[PDB]
Amino acid sequence: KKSIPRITSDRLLIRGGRIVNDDQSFYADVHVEDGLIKQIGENLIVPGGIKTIDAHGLMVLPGGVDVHTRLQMPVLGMTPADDFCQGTKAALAGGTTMILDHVFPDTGVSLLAAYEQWRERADSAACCDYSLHVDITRWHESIKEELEALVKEKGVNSFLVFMAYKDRCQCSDSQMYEIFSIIRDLGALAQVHAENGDIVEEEQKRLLELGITGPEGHVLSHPEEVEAEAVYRAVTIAKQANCPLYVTKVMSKGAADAIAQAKRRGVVVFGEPITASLGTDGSHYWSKNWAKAAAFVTSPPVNPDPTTADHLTCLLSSGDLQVTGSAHCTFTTAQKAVGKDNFALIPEGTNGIEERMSMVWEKCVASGKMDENEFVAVTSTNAAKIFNFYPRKGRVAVGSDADLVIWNPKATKIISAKTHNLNVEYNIFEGVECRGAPAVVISQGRVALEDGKMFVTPGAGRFVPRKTFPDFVYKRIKARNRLAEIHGVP
Amino acid sequence: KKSIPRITSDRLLIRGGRIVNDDQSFYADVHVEDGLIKQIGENLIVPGGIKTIDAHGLMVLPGGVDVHTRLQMPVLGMTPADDFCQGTKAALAGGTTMILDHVFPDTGVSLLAAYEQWRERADSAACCDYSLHVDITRWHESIKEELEALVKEKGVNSFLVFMAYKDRCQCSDSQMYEIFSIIRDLGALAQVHAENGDIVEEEQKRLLELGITGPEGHVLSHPEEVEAEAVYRAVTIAKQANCPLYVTKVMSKGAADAIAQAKRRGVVVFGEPITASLGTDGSHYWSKNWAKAAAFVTSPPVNPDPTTADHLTCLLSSGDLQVTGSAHCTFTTAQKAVGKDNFALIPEGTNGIEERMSMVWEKCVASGKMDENEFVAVTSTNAAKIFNFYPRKGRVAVGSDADLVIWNPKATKIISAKTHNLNVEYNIFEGVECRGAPAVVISQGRVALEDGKMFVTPGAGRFVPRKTFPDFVYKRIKARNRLAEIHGVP
Amino acid sequence: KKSIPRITSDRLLIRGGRIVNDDQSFYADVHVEDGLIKQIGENLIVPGGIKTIDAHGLMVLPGGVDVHTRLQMPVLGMTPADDFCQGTKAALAGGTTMILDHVFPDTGVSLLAAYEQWRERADSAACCDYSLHVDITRWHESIKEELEALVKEKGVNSFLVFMAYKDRCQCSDSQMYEIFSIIRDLGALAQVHAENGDIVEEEQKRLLELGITGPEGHVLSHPEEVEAEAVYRAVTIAKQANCPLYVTKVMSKGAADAIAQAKRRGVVVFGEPITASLGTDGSHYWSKNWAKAAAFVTSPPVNPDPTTADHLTCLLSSGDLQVTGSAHCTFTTAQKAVGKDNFALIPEGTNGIEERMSMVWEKCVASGKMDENEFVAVTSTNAAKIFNFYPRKGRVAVGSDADLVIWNPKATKIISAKTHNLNVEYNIFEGVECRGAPAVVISQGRVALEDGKMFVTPGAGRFVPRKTFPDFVYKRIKARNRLAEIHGVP
Amino acid sequence: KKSIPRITSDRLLIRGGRIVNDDQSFYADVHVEDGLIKQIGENLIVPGGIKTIDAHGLMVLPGGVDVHTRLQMPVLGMTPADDFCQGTKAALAGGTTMILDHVFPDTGVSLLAAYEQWRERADSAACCDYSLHVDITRWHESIKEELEALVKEKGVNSFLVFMAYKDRCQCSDSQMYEIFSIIRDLGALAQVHAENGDIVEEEQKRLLELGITGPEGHVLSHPEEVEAEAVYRAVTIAKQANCPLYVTKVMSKGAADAIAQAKRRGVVVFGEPITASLGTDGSHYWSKNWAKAAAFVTSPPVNPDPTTADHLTCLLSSGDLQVTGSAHCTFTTAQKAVGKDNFALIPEGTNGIEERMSMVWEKCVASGKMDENEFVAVTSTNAAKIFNFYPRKGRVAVGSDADLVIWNPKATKIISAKTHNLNVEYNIFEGVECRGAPAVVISQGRVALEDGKMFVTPGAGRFVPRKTFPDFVYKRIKARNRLAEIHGVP
């Protein structure tokens, strides 16, 4: 008698596609087995019976990597309406197969404890693979031990510091310098939420004092100048500390320019525009419909200058902005409405997880500013290299994870709350038409989207641990450490 | 019997000069009486006997206005070596006839009390006219009343805030915003000492930790980036508050560029390069001679990039930097030497009061970057318009004060401690040769310098009170206030 | 018997005004006699009977100096609809009292002959004072003698070179360098019409080839890039030749930025935005109404980017753009309509002479970007200093010409062809509302506008001759000549 | 009886190396067979006997691709001293395994005929693989047929246009636009030699007129401004034509900035700094030793501003400058000396082919500005993608050509004419010390350099034909063509 092992069904054959990686495009068939890309070539020898997808005339590209989601973060006591299960389903529907969610400790909760609560929730509800950033809401004298445990034991290599939310989680410049020096020693990436909280607080007061209580008060109290200044100050502190810097939620021309200028001076810095900053503008804060206007309330806000998106799109093309995220963090109209009488009480956050891939295509590729290969770079590959999971993600290559999008550059879709996969009533991209969309989405070698139908398994998604010292970040950083030593300076 | 009044001897006739104002140059004679310019013209009818100066082939221009001196400020317990009497003598020797000195309250001393101590000392020792800025070293809840008394009663219309000196006189961004809003309401000018004190403090520690205890540790702990960032943050807060901003001690390209960029965006901001930033560079911090190196220790430091001066000179030419000062604040070698073992204990401050006019001429006019008229602008006229004593100063015009320099554009002088009019042993411009120098200096209608000899009267110099709301500053500011009201915003 | 001379009636008393010069504002009465300002003061001793104007609550400022008009230039065989008489009347109605018109020699006509034809026409028809620029349409080997006669005998100190109009009046870079070297030696100002004619010609062909024959073809064939490039190339050649450069018709952000960057590098260059570039945008080229669209056809075109005007207004505020003109050159709808089937046959030119002062006030002063004093600078004073008739014009000062505007900052007017003083049916500012307008206009000491009525005398206007080597331009240029000699280089 | 085929000896095993590609580094062994990389992995199954190289502790990277050589170009009648054989030997000695040489037709010689002369010479003398750019020295009406034959039949996809050499090979702007439109239609890359020839010619005359006949006259007649302006004008014309642009010999900050600004506006443009612009400065033109100074004479010249190299190195780091070349074109002292009495008669050209890899490492990697992966990008990979031979070159990957450098980052070498592999007496990098050098160089799977000894076979090098429409260039270009069609514009 033979005892026969079971062979798992996360196997498929994709025929006829134009494979698009960040370095080149080429024509070949793709054989997936056990959730991995097993062969890439012509006239591939493959088992009969195998699920077969004909990708002819279409592209086969790595699944999107959303570098920023906030699917479980508490905001003014509110739980986001799209939780890990709905968020990751929405992600898959838009061609994203991996998300990086922000762990945000509630008051009194340590970083490790918050990390464990996130893992508990995500491991049982994630429809696609994921990993976690850890947000530092309070500095204290020994939190280096927490950071150290997180990077050595829990597969985390990025932490976020807040320059805003005065009297809550804002850091001082001294504290920032100290945290960035620790992050550097640990081989981790320093993220920032870059707005001057003290200035925001002063404007919010003045505005409320004059009865400007609607959502336009939110954008008015977060002028572009407080983002640009905070980014510049963060860059400055990071540069002095030789700590690699990652600027979250790049919403303005001024913030993006500061990053581009820093890069020209050799600063190790990354910028993250999000779907909202590429896809809409802040004119809607002044909408006669309060609920619509509130739907845009997020920090930094969607910039009211409608030339912003095109500018940000130019800087994705030139390599100054390297990754795209959503910062997806949604609240219903009822949730937003706690701030009906005071914009400062509106829970901040907006949509973007589902629209990211198509909006990036529409703004960048369909416009002629960038090509398909650059598109892969800024939607998966650069993210994978920055956060240290390349080429596991962000590459159609033998041995990589079978997270694949069969992409149709000729498809067009009008975004609407009528058809979106979110638990909220408004979509900040209502009525925007995008060129480019997924035809098929594959996650872990299984079809998640085909012929307009979703096939998801909440809890199938796995945690992806991330080693410290990613080369793409740290080779420069370590050379600069060694030079400082040789030259006897800090 | 007739009772005959005495006619005072502050009268003279200057013949044959090329009068140079900021708007034009022209040939005419100048008649001074009672310390004022009484007539300007050809074939002037004037009393026989009058002291007569032949200015033929030479220029007659307004006396310099040094917008920044620190002749009585205590630094680490040390009193500056050139006090009000020696400082103003040195000023007159270099063609400056008015100084604006900084009142700096010692700990426990109110602004009004410090103002009164400065007036007591300056009124009895000043060789030329003067006025006072008031430095705010501590924020408290009612200091608006002090500021208000100062501008309404004491002829002060400018106050300085520090962004550096952590744990001593550094303000937070909230406090800065609140002070700038008060300064705006009072019609006064907000000056800043623009360096990020928190970052400076962190670098100083790291450097001392590695035993870099010499004066190069001072420049190394105050990199250009902390000046540029602080200037940008100040500009940002000033702009939000609609408060006119004046950046003191512009020493770097980055700081100057930030101001130039702000001006292009319509921000009401002024920049003040000083003699040291136009005349030398920071290579001397690394001098084998400790005493020489220490002589350069001042904050912000003299920039080590030797292309800095030429850049600053370009921005004086383009109108982005509008005034020149000295920040003169000198300490002997023995005084500096308290920091022999720790650069952070070296009292900060350097020379420049005597060399300002000639160094500006040498760098700006003798190079062909600017003309004689622009030279007057950036050495007296702009200062007079900013601080609200135009055309009393900064103009050869009937009714203006007779503060006049007979200027020789062909003279050349090598600066040296061997011939300078200071009480210190080193000169940061040792061996620098400048084209352009005063032949005659007239203060209050009396000759102070002639044929290389000084004629000074300590205590002759008067306090010049300065009204609030100078048009050159505030017309824009007030229009913006009115527009905010019309548009129902802060 | 006494023989009694006649005393002329170009005398008046203006009481109660706020005098506004470029350097300061102040309250005083103004006494005009014989077309000159005779006294400025309080309690002025003046003849009884004198015409008296009460300017209380209003401003008294120098009459505008329009640095660019084209009132007699032939365009595609067409004579402009507003000739010297109508143009200068329209100018006076908008508070401009001096114009600088461009002499443009027809084919076969020498510069001197064209100059004489312009003088003949202008001397008998000008309602206000004027002077003449001379446009060089053809380079030849001995034209230096013409230029020399013009500056030595005919009171001309500015000449214009064309970089556009390929095969007609475009110069090559060699020729430009040679002309600029001659202009420098003569002490004259080199103006440019800065567009790349070769590129324009290639785009015009492509566009006509695809049947884009409407006025939008005109703007499409003159993209912003050809202006910016030509300005940069002109700046470059001027800098190498040490020849002062004046850029006419600054219509784009790119052109203005090039000038601002040049000034920062110490280049002697002036920029001239015009009413059209501050007051409207190029969206109207796409108007369904052909006649409206054609009304905007001029080169360089009105930029389609509607953020342009605000940018140009920022650069007037920062001092990078120093003068304002109209380039007024109007054609009726019938005249424009020769190009009904081919945009390249539409005669180029648009309005602006009447609206310049109010549009500059509206965009610059009423917005809070600039103050009243800066307004005088960029509307009269800087022009007077550049072209060498300061302080005869551009200053309320004793001995200056009595060209004065009693200006009402609170007046508002909607511009319309229904009320304009032009001979054409369209106004490119139709429906634009401006704050700020003249109440009274005085030219040569006589009232030209009062209570909404014009009082003009065609032929009263005089030619104003302009000496070479204006200091405001040439002091820098001559210093640089002397330095080149000292250093043994060109 | 068996008839046995011969197995060629271009086989080897490289063990223990850190493989460095532009996307990642990783540890693996490399098996080469038949001049190709056959396997990459651990525990590779390989024939016994095979030549084996132990690369432990060292890097294995793609051989350099020198995008610019001029080894056979005639200059003032002179043949370069390092011909194809010596040049390619020198290249291999410095870790470059592929060169792109410029075909330059002598007067009266067609492009095809010059191409055939280059192939004849290179095929029999090249020690490494090569390809050819074709320089267009004269525009004529039918030269499109030559260009077309070259790209369809002769494996050429890049052509160079000259903006300098007035009256010899300079193109006008019209001609440039027409050539760029043809190049675009053919799928080829437009290169430029970007200097304003008309301005250069005028300066050269002035300088010779004042007897400045030495080599400093060469740099003085080619100021940075003529490069920056010409690059901007080229960018402008390329953008209007939608033709991809490649700027050769980027020597100045101004030229590099123009390219960086263009990229930010979405222009398809590449920049090529060369060894000389990264490795030395133009102070040497003023050397007391004429022969040394003449050794630097090349166009554009080595910039006299010694901060230039660091700036260019920053822009390689930020991605604005993507490829590095040598422009190697050497002449002996005797050859240079024909210009002993007139700098304009000195044959232009300098060294760099041998030093490129080490100088790029020294300036970019050893300084901490860039990492090893970026180094591969700018020394081989980007070149391969631009000119359409990726991944055949520029990648350690199975199936790619076995052109490999075993690189030692810890080696240091002082460059000297005493040890260089050139036929000239001077080296413009004399005495420069570089970190980083080749230990072993492999070309076509054969060792060319080992233990400091060269092993070369003149004529082994092959011509590498290059298809049109490289994706890395043309995907953007073709999208923009399609958008123009959709929108009915050129």
Image (cartoon, coloured by chain):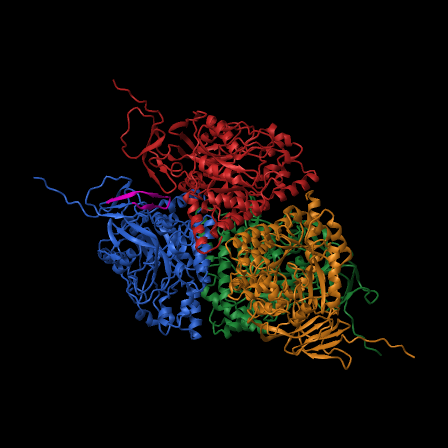
Chain colours: A blue, B green, C orange, D red
Q: Is C46 drawn above or below residue A174 in the view shown?
A: below
Rendered location of residue A52, percent (x, y): 24, 47
Q: Is residue B191 visible?
A: no
Residue placed most toward the observer, C108 or D274:
C108
Q: Is C248 drawn above or below residue B426 in the view shown?
A: below
As for residue D417 lying within the magenta part, the answer is no
Instruction: Name the side, left or right, on which C290 lies relative to A209.
Output: right
In this view, the residue farthest toward the bottom is C49
Rendered location of residue A68, percent (x, y): 34, 56
Q: Which residues are magenta?
A: A16-32
In this view, the residue farthest toward the left is A1
As for residue A30 lying within the magenta part, the answer is yes
Residue at x-position 33% and y-position 60%: A328
Q: Is A228 drawn above or below residue C21 in the view shown?
A: above
Residue placed most toward the observer, B22 or C77:
C77
Rendered location of residue D20, percent (x, y): 37, 38
Find residue A142 and report its image quarter. bottom left
In this view, the residue farthest toward the top is D1
Rendered location of residue A386, percent (x, y): 36, 49
Q: Is residue B187 visible?
A: yes
Find residue D166 and report its image quarter. top right
Residue placed most toward the observer, D359 or B148:
D359
Q: How many numbered circles does the render carry? A: 0
Residue placed most toward the observer, C4 or B406:
C4
Instruction: Name the side, left or right, on which D372 lies relative to D177.
Output: left
